[PDB]
Amino acid sequence: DASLHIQTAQNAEFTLDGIKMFRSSNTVTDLGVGMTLTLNKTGEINFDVQ
Amino acid sequence: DKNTTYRDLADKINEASGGEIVAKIVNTGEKGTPYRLTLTSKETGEDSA
Image (cartoon, rainbow over all chains, first blue to last red):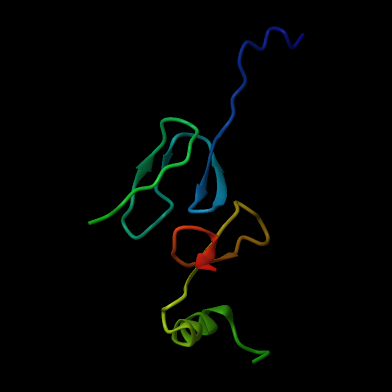
């Protein structure tokens, strides 16, 4: 019986500035260089460094 | 050249583009073929070209 499966686990997914990438959760650091990031919803966004 | 690696050509093309065209290697989360090439340019639309 699959009805007992209230909720199933799945990833968060994102682009590396154009090219997409799927990961378990809403936090990312594979960028290297010294860059860190976290996700809070499915959308498009731009960020800046100064 | 037919024997050269991407690594060597990457430095060469930065000179060939003069840095005027910006390029970098990015992944699709794609096992086996994890390299994808991105080329970028600026203006208010597709005309960046």
